[PDB]
Amino acid sequence: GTPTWQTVTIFVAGVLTASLTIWKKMG
Amino acid sequence: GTPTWQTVTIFVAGVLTASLTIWKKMG
């Protein structure tokens, strides 16, 4: 009935993590 | 560490999508 918050929180954290990994790998 | 199989699959989908969005700005 109520949606879980683990899927939404992990998904947003994955996008944020990609910023740090790509930025660090792109100099 | 070793997160559940569902967590790793969702992480790749979020990073892969974010990769395309950033690539559009870096193109």
Image: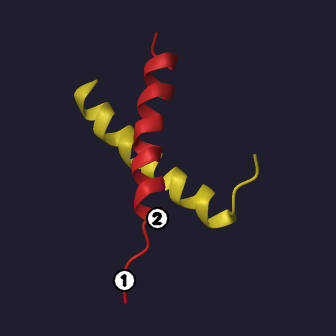
Chain colours: A red, B yellow
Q: Position of residue A18 (x, y in %)?
A: 46, 35
User: In which quadrant of the rendered view does residue A11 lie?
Assistant: bottom left
Along the horizontal axis of the image, is B1 left or right of B11? right
Relative horizontal placement of residue B21, taking residue A24 as reference (left or right): left
The tag on residue A2 is: 1
Residue type at mark 1: give it. Thr
Residue B21: image quadrant is top left
Residue that badge 2 annotates: A7
Where B5 falls versus A4 (above or below)?
Answer: above
Q: In the rendered view, would you say B1 is above or below B24? A: below
Could you give the CA–CA distance between mark 2 and mark 1, rounded to whole angstroms?
Answer: 13 Å
**Residue at image point 45% right, 16% down:** A26
- Nearer to the camera, A2 or B14: A2
Residue drawn where x is 51% and y is 18% of the image: A25
Q: In this rendering, is residue B8 above or below A22?
A: below
Is disc 1 placed on a helix, strand or loop?
loop
Q: Position of residue A13 (x, y in %)?
A: 45, 45
What type is the residue that disc 2 sits on? Answer: Thr
Asked whether, in this view, residue B22 is left or right of residue B13, the answer is: left
